[PDB]
Length: 100
Image 1 (tube, one colour):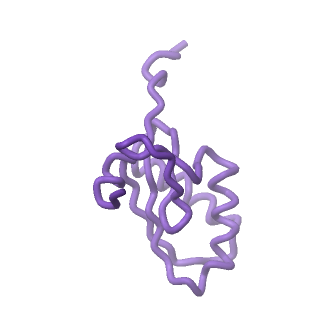
Image 2: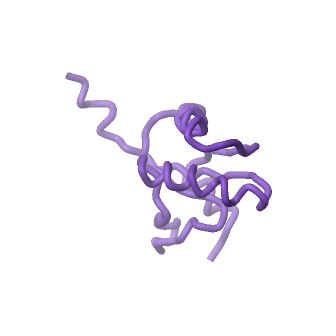
Image 3: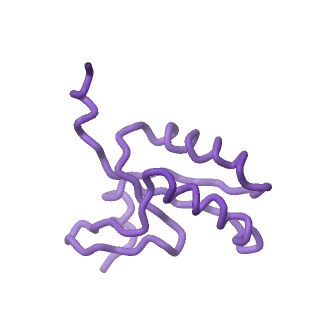
């Protein structure tokens, strides 16, 4: 079996965009994140376990960015409705914007 290849679990960050009026709605989607492989903490480039629970989140997946998107957006069928827009990026790409 192809255990190889996907022996490299990467680390991504997802930046969700949505107005605060949908926070009550989004609480469903957030619960989906942690039900999935997403996390609230990830180490930065220095090595500090950062909290993401502002706006972005992280995941140890190795699928592609638009694959993470599809994963999340198909979980939107659980929640009522929220116009959210997410940007997947790698964790490194994330912390390079938000510093110490």
